[PDB]
Amino acid sequence: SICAAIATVSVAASTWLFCRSRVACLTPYRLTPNARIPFCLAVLCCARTARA
Amino acid sequence: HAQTFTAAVSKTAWTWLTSLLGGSAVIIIIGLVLATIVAMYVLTNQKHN
Amino acid sequence: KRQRMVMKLESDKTFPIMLEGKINGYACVVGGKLFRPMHVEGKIDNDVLAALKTKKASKYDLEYADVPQNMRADTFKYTHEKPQGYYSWHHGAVQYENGRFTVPKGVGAKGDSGRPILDNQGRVVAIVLGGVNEGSRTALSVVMWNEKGVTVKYTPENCEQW
């Protein structure tokens, strides 16, 4: 149970990191005033194929 | 008797199970560092202006 | 000149953030996307835009949403050309220097959030979210975007939500 609990915490931490990672990507994406960030996505490729 | 605490066996298998724990901790440590690194990249990109 | 700038502001469609009949801020559409100050409480003065689901941005304490193409037909025009000098906004003129906007004291206050800053071409260079009294003048907390398309928020130390 101890080992499982530790792994569980690691999974939760990883998820938290992922969410913060998505924020880090979206940060520069704000909009941005332009609606055009092809090249930001092309380089970072954080995911969520955006869009058409 | 005997009756000692090694604890007890079984090498191979002992290591197999031991190795299963801590790996996920290392992963989230690496991810943590990488997240900070990316953050600094963003901060630099902002300071660029 | 300020008159002509106001005329462009009048042509530009802007919508205050209404709460209990009180304007707590402003929200508008630039580059075909809606932006709204999150720290401001209330709803935009536009049911059509209100019908749109927004996304949160804790980093900047802002929300945003995608605008229907038909509504994108006429939105605000942004530029990355941000030379030092003077710009124009709703509350008169503003000095741009060191990448920061400053105006005479007594200008700007809580509820002014969302007011953009325009150049001589009527192009957006920054958006005012807050500010802080700086002696004979006040320093504005703003967001602006460089030629790299990077969102940069300039916030004075201990800046007040204006």
Image (tube, coloured by chain):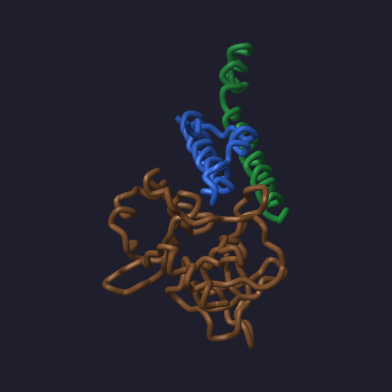
Chain colours: A blue, B green, C brown
Tell me which residue sits at (48%, 78%) in the image.
Answer: C109
Q: Can you give x and y, in whole percent of width and height, for residue A43 in the image?
A: 65, 34
Tell me, yes or no, if residue A2 can be seen here.
Answer: no
Q: Can you give x and y, in whole percent of width and height, for residue C29 in the image?
A: 44, 55
Residue closer to the observer: B19 or B3: B19
Q: Is residue A40 above or below residue C75?
A: above
Q: Is residue B27 above or below residue C32?
A: above
Q: Can you give x and y, in whole percent of width and height, for residue A19 in the image?
A: 50, 41
Residue closer to the observer: A5 or B49: B49
Q: Is residue A14 above or below residue C64?
A: above
Q: Is residue C2 above or below residue C153?
A: below
Q: Where the N terminus of chain C falls, by quadrant?
A: bottom right
Q: How many marks?
A: 0
Q: Can you give x and y, in whole percent of width and height, for residue B48 in the image?
A: 72, 53
Tell me which residue sits at (52%, 35%) in the image.
Answer: A10
Figure quadrant of residue B1: top right
Q: Give left or right: position of C31 versus C155.
A: left
Residue closer to the observer: C126 or C55: C126
Tell me which residue sits at (67%, 47%) in the image.
Answer: C148
Tell me, yes or no, if residue C17 can be seen here.
Answer: yes
Q: Residue furthest bottom?
A: C136
